[PDB]
Structures are given as structure tokens and as C-alpha cells.
Image (cartoon, rainbow over all chains, first blue to last red; front, side):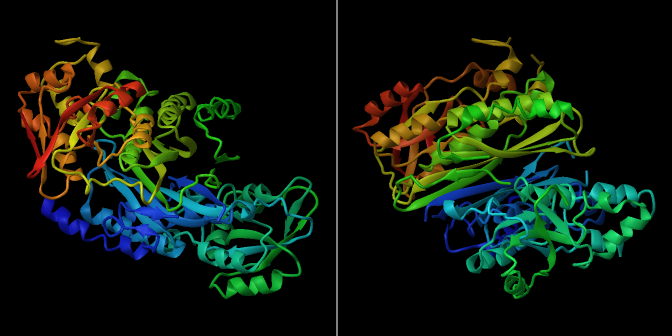
Length: 307
Length: 322
């Protein structure tokens, strides 16, 4: 039905809700190009188990933020400015409504991340799938060479700032399920999408000297925080300097899991960390609150190793 | 565990793809500090392999399709006059056999070698029961850079302009569902006129036209290019051609692989149909002036391509043969 696809195409006045000036516009901007000091490109892609909730709940308008989230947060942590987004939706038989729903959510993370949805595609893959689909994302960011923050300016004792997560985000969702497969509202919280920190960082970097940043994905703080730390340097979190979610405290009891254990799977209520010079932590903490983020002095840098 | 340090070592297929421009390594980096463009523009694109993959599950050959994935992305780039810089892959599977995944990036690297782009990143997803054991998926994503003045869209193509076609490796990457439909209706893999084992003919990877296409452009005026993919000639030649301009194709100007013949004989297809699905031996078309047409043909063949004056531009609409 090429008619239904007609009115399915016009439906993407969604993508334009992501558009930026730089887009030498194709469709609504779909298919177009991106117009471009000492320019360096930063790219990323991200295909998680968090999709399982969506298949069941049959609710797909927010799963595409997480995606955008998991791509763009990792580019901006290198102080790069996200420009455009490409999506790949592997599909049994495209449910014209489902597709549109999922791209309704992609264009919402794109708006927030402040990048254009210049392209993407729905794959009719007859056989692999029945209520399922896979969602992939691709991103390109830009940075000035001498401005890349790659935390080698991380000196012992810097104040560590932690920006507030909305819940699980995109990781741990297999342990979540087993824990509450071992057990028995739940789903609205677990369908909570991953926060995007792109805009507030950018205006942060525009104002302050950011020593280093990290995105709390991987295996919790322990994987990710040291990740930014330089040799002979460390990171000590003052437990109780931020508000941890009922979700996390919840899985802590239910599965009866260990603290240090959970800290290596789950964000434990904190989505991102940037290292800051003790004399500035105050007003930049202020600045981010000014950005609608939950900033807090989570701990500090030390000379050593780990968390 | 111990098998991953080694599987991350054999990942050296990327080393074979690298350019000076690629900057050291949460998101690969490419330097644009020496490109000497004055109105620089980024042209990107993503595509997923498709129905061809089903035949790579059958033959258990996984190191070439990645050339298929790259080729589609990259040919769609240079055809607008850009230069592919870097590529990112996304592979989806139930779970990953480090080897099998190694063969996929192995043909992704190669394809990237030929396209001349860096393999700067990629994801590998061991998925639940969403994917079976044999069954996997493969999407790619490219970025190319062009100067705002050097873009080609076809609007400048005119009546009496000369269409050259660059030959293809065979089916490339389009029409395989209809191919399979007579695999069913037919009988499976050496058939008829000049021939390899049938499956082996079918799994021939898509041609990558990048390196020649940029050399062209460095030496001559190109008014259009069409990547003959989905919808074959009937879909893709029209789309480069402005209003009032149609196309005349001279059926004997190029070589049609026997598999297209087979498919038509065996499948009882019409020629119009065939040309609305299959490339029929020509993977990419480029409108040219008449006065250059013959130089261009040799520049391309000096490039290592097979290039034929395939037809011409007229007043009208769509495509017409003779």
C-alpha cells in the first residue's frame, strides 16, 4: 500500500522537529547533508536488552531516546558537539504505526541532544522476527583538536561532579529481570528513558574549564570512572552525596545484592561525572543546576587507583 | 575471556583501512584540519545488507558480504560527488562466535580498503532469541565530505548528454528475494551459459566504484551519476534526470551476465520487469558531455573498471531502450 506509505512519509514532520540550520535539507531534512575551526570529527554507534520491556508493553515512543542518549552522551563527554543522527531499525514486517512511534522517540532524543535526524532506515527482514525489532544508532560530533577533553589534565584532588540519572538508564536490565524473574509501578520506572546531558555540558564547556568527563554506562562507576582517571590518580565517592533511586535500593534488597557489586553494573542514581577544579566546583555546580541537571559534589580525585 | 584479547588482536582488519587523518585510539576521531575545502559539506548514509545475507547462512561464507554492506553505503556517497571518510558497522546476532564475527569485519575492512574509508568504529550485539544461531544482521554507516560547489545532482544534465555505464559484478545487492523464489521454483547450486557454481555466482560481492569515481571528477565535468540499486534502471536513471529529460538505452552496448539471462529464462520474466529489479550488468551510470565520452571511458578502464557508452539523454521522461 503506497498510499498508506504516503501518509506514513508525511508523518515524518517529526524529523524536522530535530532539524538544525546546517542541514542542507533533503526531505523534511531527511536525506540531506550537513554544512561545516581546526575541525575534528567524533563518531559513535550503539545497538540494549532494555528493548525487552518495549516488546511486552507495546510502548515504543520513548525507547529511542535511550538510544540517542547512549550515543550522544559518549561523544559530548569528549567535549564534542553532536551534529546529526542516523537510525537503523531492523524489522520483521514494518508496522507503519510502530515505526513512526519509534521514530517519534528518536526525534525527541535528537531535539534534546540538539542534533539533526538526517537519515536512517527500517529493515524488512522477513524471518528473523515476532513482536520484536532491533534499534541501532549512529552519531557524528565535532570538536576543536586542542579542545578535546581527554582527562590527562586530571590532577590529584580535583573535585568530582556527578550529574543525576533518572534510573537504570540503559544498563543492568538483564540483572533487573533475573532479580525480578526471581521475584515478581515497576514497568513505568524501568521504561524510564536515559537522560541526555549534551546541552548542559556544552554550555558548561562554554563557560568552565572541564578537566575530564565520564558517562556511567559500562560496568558502573568502577568501570567508567577510573576509565577517565590517569595513572597514579584515583577517585573517592562520598557515599551519601547524591540521591539514589528507589529502583536501585529496591533491587538491592530483592535480589539481596552487594553494594560494591551493584556499583559495577548500575549507575546507582548518577549518570555522568566530570572532574572539576576545587575552586570552581561551586559555581559550575551552580551552572548545571541552572541547566536543569542535578549537580552535586560526589567525591574527589586522589592519587592512587580505583573507587 | 582469554579468547577476547586474541579476538581483539585479529581485529587488525581495521589497520588495513586507516588514513593519516584518523586520530588515535568512546568515539573514533577523524581530522578535518587539512582538507582545503572552502564550503565543506558532510554527506552521510546508512544501509542494511538485506536478503543476500540468507545465502551467506547457507554457504557458511561470511567474509565477503561485509564488502556488500560497505559498497552500498559508499557508492551512494560518491555518486553525489563526495569522498567517503569513515565507516561504522553494526552487527546483530543471538550471540557472537569470535571467529564468525571476525570474518564479517574481515570483509568489512576489505570493502573499506577499496572505498578508501577508515573503519573507525562498530558494535557487536549478542542478542536473545530475536536472532537464531545462523541468522545475523549487518548495517553500515558512512560519512563523506564534499565541497558545496562540487556537488552533483543531475539538474545540470542535458539533452544530448552521454550516459556511460560502469559494469557490475553481477546481482550486486538487490533482487535476491526474487532470486530465491526461483531457487524454490527452480533447483539449487553450474547452470547454463558461462558459469561458476550457482551459489558462488550469487554470493559475488557488490562492486565498489569509489576510487575510480573520484579520479574521474578530478579530471572531467560530470553532470550526474546514478547508483543502479533497487528498482534497477527504471528507478535510478530517471532520478538523476531533471524535467523534460528522459533516457535512451541501447540494449547491446554492454555485457549482461548469464545469471541475468538465467533468471529471465528460468523465471519467465519480461525484460521490462527484469530492468525494474536487476542492474542487468551495470552498477553505476554517469551523464557526461558527448565530447569527453571516449576519454572518460578510458580513464575509468585505466582505473580498473569496465566502462561503456550505454545510451543517451533526450527530451521526455523516464527510461527507454532500443
